[PDB]
Image (spheres, rainbow, N blue to C red):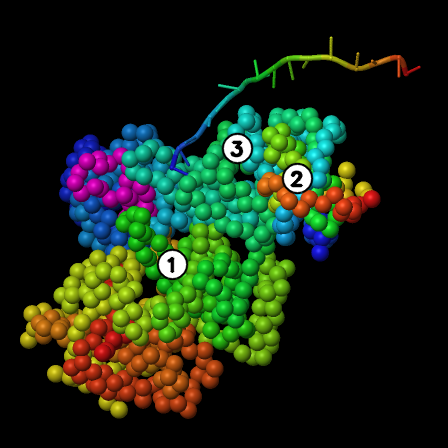
Amino acid sequence: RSWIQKVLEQIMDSPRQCVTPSEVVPVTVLAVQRYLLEDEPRDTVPKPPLYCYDVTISDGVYQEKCYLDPSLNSLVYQNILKVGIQMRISRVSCLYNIGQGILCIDNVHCGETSDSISLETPFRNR
Amino acid sequence: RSWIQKVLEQIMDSPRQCVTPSEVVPVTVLAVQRYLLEDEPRDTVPKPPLYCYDVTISDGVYQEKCYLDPSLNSLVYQNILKVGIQMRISRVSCLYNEKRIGQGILCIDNVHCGETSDSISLETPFRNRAHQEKPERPLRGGKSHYLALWNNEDPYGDIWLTDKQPEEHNFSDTKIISLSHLEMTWTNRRNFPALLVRILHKSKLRYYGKPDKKMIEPYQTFLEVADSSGTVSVIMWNALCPEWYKSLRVGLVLLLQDYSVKKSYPFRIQPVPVDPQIKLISTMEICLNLRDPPTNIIIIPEKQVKPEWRLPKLNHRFTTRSELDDMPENCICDVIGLLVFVGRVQRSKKKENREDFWSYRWIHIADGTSEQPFIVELFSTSQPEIFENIYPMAYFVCTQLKVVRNDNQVPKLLYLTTTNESGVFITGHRGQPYTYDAKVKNFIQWIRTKSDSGEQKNMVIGGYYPYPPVPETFSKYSSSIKVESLLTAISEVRKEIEDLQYREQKRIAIQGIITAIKYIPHSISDRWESQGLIDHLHYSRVYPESIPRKFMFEHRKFLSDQYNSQPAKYVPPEGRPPKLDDFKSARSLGHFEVTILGLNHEIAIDVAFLPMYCPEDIRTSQIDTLLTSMNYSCAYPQDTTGNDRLPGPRAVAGDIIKAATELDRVHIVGILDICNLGNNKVEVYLHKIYSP
DNA sequence: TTTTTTTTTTTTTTTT
């Protein structure tokens, strides 16, 4: 039923090797919040971004907070990934940075402004 | 003392001058190799051949590796100049290699190739020790190498090493990144860290050595290795291929370092792997050139492998005949089963280069899921040791086979082809290398059960097997021939037969009337006629090699060598061999000598009709007509009973004669396969007599 | 298809 539920159970069942969402449905961004990127190797030649973000998607059933891949920080730098806009994830992982997990977004296709953004959908994870 | 010594002493002091040898003594050919003809002037209107040949003629005393003047390559294209033959050199010349310190080279310039020698000695000493250098190389050139005698996709010579073994490289402080990491960051990484990849597909060799450009080992192989989720088409360059190709098998965990990353070649077609979950990185490709230190390629043993990391396992798409019955046009698949037929080494000219050739051989793989085999089109997969030596009574597995279907004709052409990444192997008695697969287990169980039932399959080797069956609709046959002169001239057959090279195949159509037919029992009237021409062709000769032979394990090397490709070097017979005729013929009915009259009653031709259908076919009406050469099964009789209560093959004979008699003056377009079996022997056989 | 070597990078916190 719920897209986030299906994705979570799928990545739990199949190996969590950047599982591609079996089904892709537009999802509405409800929040984009930033914090410092701690606990990173920071030794690669392409040094990682200093800050990371935690998008808050909503599939109409539940709203789940997802840790955006730092590689996709340009989309938020350019204000292409803002509130309201409905996106379409194309890759997902299951990080454990553990209790339940941290649904990670490895790719996304930012869409157009949504007309049915609901602030009433309860959080799947309390 | 010896002819070699006398001629060399006579012509040593006159380089690049042609002198008839003082004495013409027959000399035995002990080896014939082929390599590129660079360094020749490509300004002559008749551009010199793209390849030259070296022949190791042997006298009674010594054998001195000579050089065949490229103008004589015609004698090798027709395989008239083969190993074990006796020839009488008529013209010689001396050439000195200016990139090597050595003596003169005998330059063969005219020969009169005769017949096989009575006594061939493989122990005659080498006059010039330089010719005996263990890493054998061509006489001309500095760092040249010999290619395979006929095809260019088969490793040949001593440059190809098999010494590579697993090495235990410590992973203490090795910086290993993922393929996706390069995909995202390879245009900014000044240095590319180490990698830990695993081979998924290994491609067939590819020779890109043009004659003018100066290259060393123009050999290039594409390996689809996958580290973690990512997969890229690694491509080895230059002289790296002949140091790692005969050793790297699919499924070896490679550790590549000091590599290069570039853009994917525009005309590259990366093959999809079995697992879809992986990422197919198709933007950048890793190039492995030969670095001065031998650390660029290091293979780590499976024990050193750590499940702690994720490495893509080698999967397969094993399919049975029943599954193939429904598989679509193009769907790459793997096949396994008991070989039940082996064809000949047919050669088809490449459209890219009219001088190069392919080397395919039609094979049949048997299984328990159907009464028909897979009918695979097996090209040379850069595995001569297996390709040449395959025989029916064994377990054979081929991977990455592309389905090919054609419903334009009634007998659906459900057969397979070998793609670039297709590999060949002969599994053990129990199937040890592929035992892990379930389909492999099923096949082994089927073979064990059938053997425990005291049953054997009809095993056939070589012969005349034109798998492609010409349709029943002459209109469709013409449609497949798009403005290519579908009907060859009755007087052109001579020229076409003169154009085929060694084991070349070609299909043409002739227009004429059935002059007559004489039945030739394989061993009811025996002969019949329909009834002064401009000229007539006598091509109704069926060679012993053309008749398929029932396989007997006791004599397997002999049978496999009678339908293989001609060897490059000599190998003395291991005793007195048997005769090909003493082996029973898999054909159940004899051939015919149908003679065709030209439409204008001016040119005639003699052709042989060698049917493959059994009396069971003419009873069950599995064939198209009585003038066809292949049954709808296109499979040699399964010998379910060997001999049935059906009309005997002698009855089918005479019946075919009268069937032809029906086509007394009927205008027909017969499809006549023409092939050059070697030497000057050429076969012209009938396929199907299209009638209105 | 060919095709190798080289490095460059600046900046405002802690006290127990």
When the figure is inspected, residue B582 is found, relative to residue A1, above or below; the finding is below
Residues at marks 2 and 1, common chain? no
Quadrant of the rendered image containing residue B532: bottom left
- What amino acid type is highlighted by mark number 3? Tyr
Q: Percent position (x, y) of residue B363? A: 43, 65
Chain under numbered label 2 = A
Q: Which mark is in front, 3 or 2?
A: 2
CA–CA distance between discs 2 and 1? 62 Å
Residue B46 drawn in magenta: yes
Residue B64 included in the magenta stretch of the image: no
The residue singled out by tag 1 in the image is B360
Region rendered in magenta? B33-59
Asked whether disc 2 touches disc 1, contact meaning CB atoms under 8 Å apart, the reply is no
Name the foreground residue: B124 vs B406. Answer: B406
Q: Residues within 10 Å of mark 2 (few under 14, many from 20)?
A: many
The percent position of residue B647, horizontal first and vertical second, equals 36, 90
Q: Is residue B22 left or right of residue B433?
A: left
Whether residue B160 is visible: no
Label 3 and label 1 in one chain = yes
C-alpha gap between disc 3 and disc 2: 46 Å
Q: Residue at x 11, y 71 (%)?
A: B603
Callout 3: SS: loop
- Which kind of residue does numbered mark 2 sit on? Gly
Task: Check the image and report above or below for A92 versus B495.
Answer: above
| Numbered circle sitting on residue B550 | none
Residue under pointer 2: A84
Name the residue beneath numbered marker 3: B259
Q: Nearer the viewer, mark 3 or mark 1?
A: 3
| Residue B630, x across and y down, in percent | 34, 74
